[PDB]
Each structure stands twice: as structure tokens, then as C-alpha cells.
Amino acid sequence: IEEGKLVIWINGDKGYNGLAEVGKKFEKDTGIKVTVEHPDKLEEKFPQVAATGDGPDIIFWAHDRFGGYAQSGLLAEITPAAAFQDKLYPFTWDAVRYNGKLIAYPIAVEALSLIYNKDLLPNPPKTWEEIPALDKELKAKGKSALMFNLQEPYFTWPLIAADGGYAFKYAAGKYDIKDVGVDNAGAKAGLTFLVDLIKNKHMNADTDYSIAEAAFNKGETAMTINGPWAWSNIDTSAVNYGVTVLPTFKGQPSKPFVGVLSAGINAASPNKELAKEFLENYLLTDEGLEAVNKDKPLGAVALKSYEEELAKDPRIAATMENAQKGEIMPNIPQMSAFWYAVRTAVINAASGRQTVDAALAAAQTNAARAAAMSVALASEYQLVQNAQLPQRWSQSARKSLAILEATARKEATAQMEAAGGSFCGQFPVDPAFKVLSLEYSAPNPDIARAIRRVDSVPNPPLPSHVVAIQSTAVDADLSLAMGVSLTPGRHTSYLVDARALQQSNSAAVAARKADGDKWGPACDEMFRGCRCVTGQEVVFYTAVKEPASLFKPSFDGPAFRPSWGELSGKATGVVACVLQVPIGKETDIICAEYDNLVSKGQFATVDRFGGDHTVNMTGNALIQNDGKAISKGYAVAHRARVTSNVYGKANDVSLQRLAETVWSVVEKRLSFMPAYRDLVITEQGKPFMLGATATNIISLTENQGVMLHLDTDDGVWTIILWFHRHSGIIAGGEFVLPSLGISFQPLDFTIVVFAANTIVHGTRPLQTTGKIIRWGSSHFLRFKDVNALAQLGAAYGVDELDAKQRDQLEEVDAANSKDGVGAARRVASCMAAERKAAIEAQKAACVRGVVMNPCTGRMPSLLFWQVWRKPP
DNA sequence: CGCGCGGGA
DNA sequence: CCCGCGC
Ligand SMILES: [Fe+2]
């Protein structure tokens, strides 16, 4: 975020061009440019980007999300003067309070109202109880009294709450998540009246949003229930309509939920006081809200002076009236427990699957249980973020290891002189040069061997934020504290400043976007500054300074005393390691499994990043797109377990060996890897990993470049390997880590292990001469699949998934033989809906395959941070 | 292999 | 919209 500027995020369905005019008027008076953007998935994108000290200066969203944001410290406490607070309705300030602190400015107010057809019904009923009689007369005329969305509890809640239902009890400025108000007498009476309407055929259990909107907008029903977002569509229709206060129930007002569109200030913003004056003196004025409202209407508004103007529209007045009779939507993440439980209960009470009593009793206990587990998971997550490696570090152990490392450096130097140079396999290694292209030979049917540097340039120097560690003492410090044990005397360790690492990450993404999501001239310019480490074994540690960010070390953790004073007040984590695997039995096994899975047709071909490149995938996916998928694997894997006439599990044995052999090679150098696996894979997720690894998906590419990118929904560390087939020369195709300032050509069997959702990376396009093929493959954790599979396991039994898969393949085929392609798709669609409903139930019970950040919905940015402190 | 159909969202 | 699937 740039100081001296203001960037605003607001959803695309709002008047952003009108807001831009307020910023343009702001830029005139003070010289501060205001940029309004409307990113997609704004509710998801803001907590992900704000948690890293980045993102907008101001966020516009429904107030209910902002308590979640405040729990994570993403929002600044706003400080309106008492005079300014008087300009806005009191209840709107209540909607933007967390922990007794104001955390946002209210802007607009929305709630459900009663919408009625003036020709069908000149005087709409003041009470719910009149509606059955009124419906009887309208039925005689070929109409109905009322249709509205019964599928979503947002729409049915006003009736359920009228006589006493509530979500979470509010007291002393806090929501008590132990106190859910779904099971009291008022809620029961509300839901009962609703189902009595259905039972007496006044309403249909099937009516959803689309059916009710189409019915009201065509003149078929006299009333609906909807919010101000629905008025535009009625305004194109022929219906003469009004908007009024919801009916009462037992003489009590219906209590719709109230959503307050609010502007909050990013905690990481350097422009807090500028954002405050823009919001107070420019937006929250009559002129300000007008400019927005003219673009797209705000509805009702929190600013009293402008709301008195808007309320001349009876639809606005009704909106604010129902809002003031309503229930401010609770601003805590545990509302998700509430929504799922009440949605289920209303659907079951309406269909007859449960009585009202049974439906609400289960919703009460299930929402409270789910809300509780949500808290337990959120506190458990802080423990995994702050967890420490088994302690092997000590001053005594540091020194012993330094001496061993120092001995090995002399051995390596001796056999370097004896041999005439440095080699990785048969490839001559010279750090003075950058390997722009290189030759491979294939003398026998084993893997092709890197033999000769062809094109080169002088090797660029390390960027300023990356420094090679010279000291065996420092090397031993980091090796013991970080769980890294590279080839003694034949590796280089680097320290990378965390702040500069983050900036360089941003510069790299900027370049890729400026190039048109491709390796173009901006990416090439970065590449020309990358230092080649081809043939080397290296590890990069990032050092985070103690806040006197992308990375979240716990500076309350145990501290070691570094040999190097410059580590003091810093925490280190492992962001990347490059290994060179000597060819032998393990590379034989790995290469053979890739060949077996290719020959047997077990790779699913897919395209990534649009059409950036082609990737083949295998492993324990769950492609929910495939309606009949109900077990681990791509569709080819599901089929092979049934159609094989030899051994149904053969490919699962092949995949486990493939994952475990790669894992084993890596674990020998990187002892933190099994600790990471043990820390983040749940008991419920373990059966859906490939063997005893943190890998569930394996990719495979063939002579493919990949644009620079961050992965997002993968694990904390990713493994990538390469191996070659046939002879030839490869130009380009480097793996590039531009935020670390390095790149390399893969040789006989190079592996990189790195933090793929945190370190930008990609692969340059290549040109080949001869038959040479460079095979690349990622082993990674794609946590969506393991979560959905862990959820399916809890619903049906882990071992029952193969039987379900078998049956579902069998009856999709039967439909295709009997009634053709269209019937088969109908059966698969029914299977998907059954599957979906099973997954949601288990997801609602907090069944999980991996531990995840509740705020970001992603895995931690790093693990196993070690704090260093050198007191004098 | 291309393009439709599809789920989740 | 997208490191699927099938005619
Ligand atoms: Fe990647």
C-alpha cells in the first residue's frame, strides 16, 4: 500500500463510478489520487491480502464480515467525533462495533420488506394471520396471496424471529456463541405458522428465489418478500407494486436481518487519517452519497440527512422501517454454523422430514456444537503456526557440526582439485557462468545425462537482499534449527531479507501481468538479473525482523543464541531448497513409476491458467465436476479399479511408491518435511494422502514453460522434480525464483522444495534440438480434495467409497445403454446432489483433512519459525 | 482432439 | 471460471 494515496475496494454491483467521482472531487481539494477498484471474490480476497499487510486502504462490504476481520486485526479502530456520530442513525453504529470498538463507517442499510401488487391487493395485510383467508379469495380468482423464497433462511427468518427467535444472544457488547435462539417457543411458533401455510396449500415447499420472482413479476401472486435489489426487475415489468412493513405475527413485528454496507480502514494502511477525512467529509455527506446513489441506488442510508431525502420514496421508508424493527446480522464467523443448521431445519420442517419441534431442537444443538468447534479449531491453528521442530540445536551441537562441515569443505576442495573442476553428475559446474542452454546424452536406456554447457553468459550477481552464508558456524546454526541437512561441504546457504522478498514477489507478478500473463520482455528483464545455481545444492532461509507482513513468526517463541549477531531480533524460515539427486536406485524407481502411469493411461490431461500450458495430473483428486465421482482419484483411476482383470489396486500401489520414494529422497536432506506432514494432515486426511507423505496430487509436464505465479490452494511446501529422456540440446526452460534472485537448469535429477504459495516461480519457454524431452513434475498438497474426501469418509466410511464408486459407475453405464447419453447425465447429476449434501453435512460438523487458516481459508505461509536473540 | 456439458460457487 | 469428463 502506497503512502500518499488511497485505493478503495467495493463490490462490482455497487455504484463504484459514483464513488470514483467522490474520489475525483477529493483529489481536487487535497491532491490525493483515489483509485476505486471492484475485484472479484472481494469477500474472500480482502482477508487473504490484508493479512499480508497489502490490499486496499478502504474496504466496502456488509458489516457482518467485519467482526471476523477485526478478530484477525485487519481493521483500524476508527475515531469519529461525537458530533460526527450524531449524523448517522444510532443502530448503524451498533452494526460496526467489535469488542466495544468502532471498526467501520456505516454507509447504507438494507432489510427485507413486503412487496405487494396494488391491483390484486389495494390494502396489504398488516398481519401474517390474515394471509390464509386472503389466499382463499385470491385462489378463487386464479391467484395466490404470497410467494417468496422458502429455500434460504434469510428469507424465512423474519417470521421465525418475530415472536422470539434469535441467532446468538448479544450482551455486554459481545455475541454469546453458547446461546443460540433457534429452539425457544417464539421460534417454534413462527416456523409452525410457516409450515401450516404449506400444509394448507397456501404456499409450496418448493418455491425458491427464481420461482417467486417470476411469479410476482408476472402478476400471479399478490405479495412477495424481497429486498431493494429486486426492485429494478419489478420496474421493467407491468406490475403496479408497493413496498411496505412486513406483516406482524402474534402482534410482534417480523424481524428481518439487517445488513449495513460499511467502509473499514485497513490496519496496514499508512493513510489512515486521509481515509478518515475522505469518509467523513466527502463520502458521508448529501453530495457524497448522492454521487454514489445516482450511479447505482444505495437503498436506505445511514446518514440521517440524506435518508430523510431518500425516504420520500415510500420503498426506502419501508426499508428503513423494517430495518429498525429487525435484527442486526451478527458480525462473527460463527454465523455460518447458524445458517447451515437453520437452512436444514426449515427445509426438513417444510417437507415433513421433521416436525417443527424436532427440526429446531437439532438445529439448536448442531449450531452450538459447530460454533464451539469453530472456536477450538481457530485456537488449534495458532498452535500449528507457532509449532517448533524437535530441538537438535545447541551451542555444543552447533560447534561440532561446524567442524564436520569445515572438514567436508576441505575434502570437496581436495577432490575438486584432483578432478580438475566441480561436477554435478557428468555436468561441469562453474558458478562464473549462467547456463543458457545445455546438451544431454542418452547412451543407454537409463535417464538422459546432462553433459555439456552450450550457450552461456557471465553469471549475474546475487541481488542485494540475498547473501550467501560464509561461516560454518552460521551454516550449522541454521541447519540444526531449521531441519535442513544438505550434502556436507557441497552446498550453499543463503539468507534473504523478508521485506525485500515480499517486494520482489510483487515486482515479479507485476512483470507477468505487464507481459500479458506470459513470459514477455518484463519477465525476461527480471530473468537477466537472476543468478544461475545450475548444478548446485542450495537452501534459502528468509529472515523476518521483529516488529519493533506475509510471514507470521511468533516472537514469543523459544529463542536460540546465534553465532552471527545480525540474526538477533529475527526469525528464520525455509523458503526454498534445491537438491541434486545422484542417479541410482531411487531415481530408477521414480522414473519407472512415471513411465508405468503414463503407459497405463492414468494421467488426466488438463490445461492450467487458461491455456498457458498443458499439464497431466494423477493422484488422489476428487473432481466434484464429475457427478459420479465419489472416491479418490481422477476418472481414469476410478475405472481401472473396476475394469482391471489382474489387480484392482495396482495404480494405488504405483502412486504410493511414487510419492513415498520422492518423499524419502527429500526427507533425508530436509528433516522438517515429515514434521510438516505430521503437523498439518489430520487423522481423517491421512487415508487420502499418497502414502505417508504430504502429497496428494502429482503433475507431469513435457517440454513445457509456465508463467510466473503463486500457487494458492496448495500446501506449505511443494516438491518439483525433473528428469530427461533422449539426447539433444535444451535452450531456455529454466526454473526461475525471481524473488530469490536465482534460476537454474535441471540436470540429471534436480529437485526443488519450496514454499509455493509464498514464493513466485515459473519456468521459461524452451527450444530443443534433437529428441530430448524434459519431464517436469510437481508433488503437492491440494487441500480441497483431501478435505472433501475426508468429508466423504466420515459420511460413508473410508472403505465403502470403492463400493459406492463401483455402483455409481455401474448404474451410469446402465442408463447410458438403456436410455442413452441424456439419461446417464441425469443420473450423474442426481449422484452429485446426493454427494454434495453429504459433504456439506460433514463440512458443517467441521470434518477436515488438513488444518487451515480460518481467516484466509489457506494453509500457513510458512512453518517452524526459529527466533534468534543475542543479548550482550 | 474438439467441443458440449457439467459441479461448485 | 477452472492442475475435468466424455461424445
Ligand atoms: Fe507452481
Image (cartoon, coloured by chain):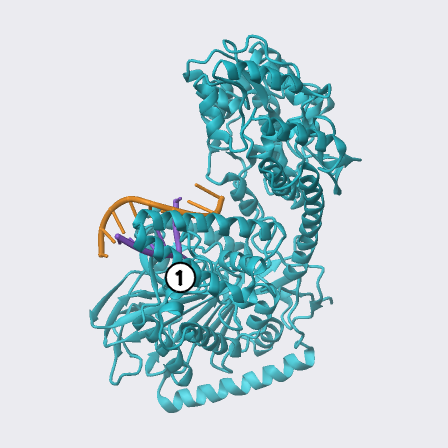
Chain colours: A cyan, B orange, C purple
Amino acid at circle 1: Tyr
Tell which residue pokes out farthest to the left in this image. A770
Is A620 situated left or right of B3 in this image? right
Which residue occupies 46% across, 29% down?
Answer: A210
Residue A498 vs A258, above or below: the answer is: below
Residue to which mark 1 is pinned: A634
Residue A328 versus residue A567 in the image, above or below: above
At mark 1, the secondary structure is loop
The answer for which chain carries disc 1 is A
Q: Nearer the viewer, residue A349 or A243?
A: A349
What residue do we see at 46% from left, 39% from top? A40
Which residue occupies the foreground of this view, A820 or A840? A820
Residue A262 seen from this side: no
**How far across and how far down the image is residue A105, in percent?**
63, 29
Within 10 angstroms of label 1, few (less than 14), some, or many (20 or more) residues? many
State left or right for residue A287 relative to residue A846: left
| Quadrant that contains the C terminus of chain A | bottom right
Q: Would residue A176 appear left or right of A273 to someone viewing this image?
A: right
**Residue A851 lies in quadrant:** bottom right
For ligand 1, which image quadrant applies? bottom left
Where residue A145 appears, x then y in whole percent? 55, 18
